[PDB]
Image (cartoon, rainbow over all chains, first blue to last red; front, side):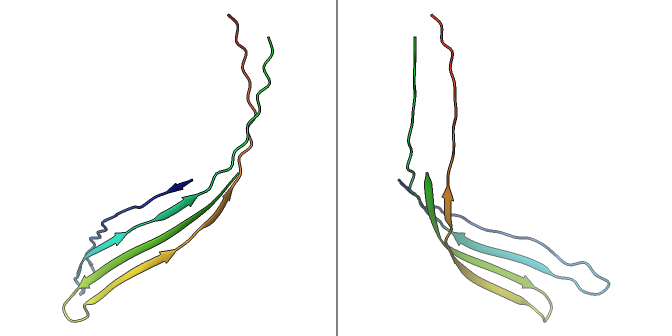
Length: 49
Length: 49
């Protein structure tokens, strides 16, 4: 089994360019995650000599 | 065999600075994924000492 925890910072930057319109943009953000993997495995090995 | 639950929490933020039509959007997020992953392996080895 595996349980995780993530952090993140986000950003964006885009300005406008038209015949009349100008602009600008900034941002933020914090993202996380909680992944719960439950892995069930089986194996076989048949060796000879 | 593996069946994975990946829960997510998240926070989001955007803005668009302009003259008078300035737009902003802070936000968040919540998500899960029910990912059932199987994997079938067949292998070999030929060792000689």
